[PDB]
Length: 89
Ligand SMILES: CC[C@@H](c1cccc(C2CC2)n1)N1C(=O)[C@@](C)(CC(=O)O)C[C@H](c2cccc(Cl)c2)[C@H]1c1ccc(Cl)cc1
Image: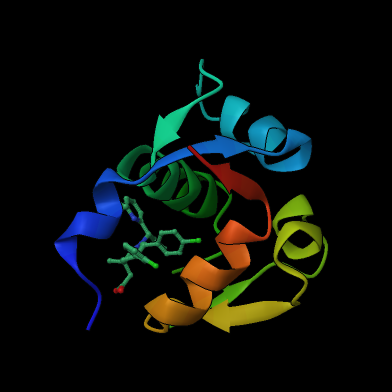
């Protein structure tokens, strides 16, 4: 399925994603996917976009991902949407 190795991937977020990350404390320009996933996860919970569907129709997350919603259990799909907003190091 999804390898644990993916969490070690080094990435450089594009401007829009970087802006979202910085709203939950992100201080850097290069991150590990583990960091990106956590910061996104915290952005999601603190904004009560989730409580298995995440609703992001009127949130920058929705513009970032290109969807009005998505399931938190569909990890492969989530990884794809995230990569649309970053560059691998
Ligand atoms: C929506 C809450 C959030 C969440 C909240 C707080 C901390 C974390 C840390 C795991 C990063 N995640 N979260 C979860 O709570 C999980 C358990 C949902 C699940 O499968 O039941 C896992 C989920 C995840 C983890 C790793 C890779 C992918 Cl693609 C998805 C993860 C998540 C979901 C969506 C995004 Cl965009 C980013 C991270």
